[PDB]
Image (cartoon, helix red, strand yellow):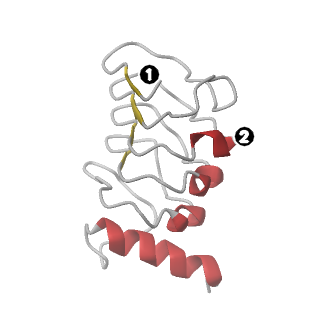
């Protein structure tokens, strides 16, 4: 199952990468769902080929620290998640990301000095990986 789109449904919980049988998962679209907790704790490497993960307009609370394991993301749309507060440092390893929409995202971590360029956000998090004072 390469691509899957289930946008604008009423999805409560998507399962973690251990429940899915496929191995070529390359695009997941789940915008406009009632999703609370993105689960990536167990065997997050199975989604290592994902190249698009949209979760906009959900009830996401916190991006898991294991999100850095999805080393091949090119887009990640976690926009319009009001309850979302700050990005984890470990996200800085997604070196192939080129799109990271931040519209209507009241972030605790200040990137007003950075701006909106996604690569800058990623490099900033990558530097905060080494040391943060």
As drawn, is 15 to the left or to the right of 60? right
Residue at horizontal 63 percent and vertical 83 percent from the top: 130
Q: Residue at x 33, y 32 (%)?
A: 57
Q: CA distance from mark 2 to mark 1?
A: 24 Å
Image quadrant containing the C terminus: bottom right
Towards the viewer: 116 or 51: 51
- Residue drawn at the location 44% of the way across and 52% of the way down: 73
| Residue drawn 57% across the image and 47% down it | 48
Q: Disc 1 marks which residue?
A: 34
Q: Is residue 84 left or right of residue 64?
A: left
Of labels 2 and 1, earlier in sequence is: 1
Q: Nearer the viewer, residue 79 or 107?
A: 79
Place residue 23 in its image quadrant.
Answer: top right
**Crowd class of label 1 (few under 14; some 14 to 19; many from 20; radius 10 Å):** some
Residue furthest top in the image: 10
Residue 108 visible in the current orientation: yes
Q: Which residue is mark 2?
A: 43
């Amino acid at each position: 199952l390469r691509s899957l789109d289930m946008s604008s449904n009423d999805i409560q919980y998507l399962p973690g990468p251990a429940h899915w049988k496929s191995l070529n998962l390359r695009e997941l679209l789940f915008s406009h769902n009632q999703i609370s907790i993105l689960d990536l704790s167990e065997k997050a490497y199975l989604w290592s080929r994902v190249e698009k993960l949209h979760l906009s307009h959900n009830k996401l609370k916190e991006i898991p620290p294991e999100i850095g394991c999805l080393e091949n993301l090119t887009s990640l749309d976690v926009s319009y998640n009001l309850e979302l507060r700050s990005f984890p440092n470990e996200m800085g390893k997604l070196s192939k990301i080129w799109d990271l929409p931040l519209d209507e995202l009241h972030l605790n971590f200040d990137f007003k000095h950075i701006g909106c360029k996604a690569k800058d956000i990623i490099r900033f998090l990558q530097q905060r990986l080494k040391k943060a004072v």
